[PDB]
Amino acid sequence: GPMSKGEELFTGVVPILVELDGDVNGHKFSVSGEGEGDATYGKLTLKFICTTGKLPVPWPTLVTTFLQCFARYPDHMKQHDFFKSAMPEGYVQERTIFFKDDGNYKTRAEVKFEGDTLVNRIELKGIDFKEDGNILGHKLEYNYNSHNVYIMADKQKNGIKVNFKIRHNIEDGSVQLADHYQQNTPIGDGPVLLPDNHYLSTQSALSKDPNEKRDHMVLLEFVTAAGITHGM
Image (cartoon, rainbow, N blue to C red):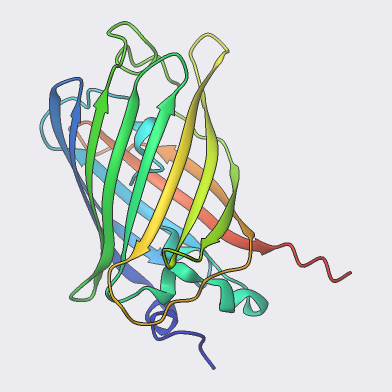
């Protein structure tokens, strides 16, 4: 049987909405996204448009901010799926992202069902970025590397936490590190699944829509959980 009510909400393809309100170094911007997720296969397909004009930061720097409830949790790990267990009421996802030798993003998001759509609504604030740096200078290549992140329960606050470093390729062959600190809290009061320590493995591909004039990003992702019981 299912390990949570929310688990049952992801057995098929689910429509997704993303809305982001951003302010980086005083530049306000808005992004809207639409797409589909299929947690049976850990897959996400999304398209994002900057509705205020040109995006003042590089698209790759917002990938982690723009849905871990769509991770594929294999059968022997469904008891560790916090993200679906918080649904439908959802969870708050808070981060600070520290860009090495540059500014920081602070983000607060709510991920929940609204009607039949899984919706991620984000407030992002960035400060202390260098005008001529990798971020405001758009020096990041339009690609994305794979990353494995270590999920841990936050027993006292009834949620999960994770730290991880994103490596962004720069146009000169160097890397821009984006150090992520993340805290997830249920929105509702019902029971949730607090996981054993485990990994989420994510692969991401960035592309463009040939028919899209606006500044935009097409994002395809594969996310799967991997346990470390090592029963051998």
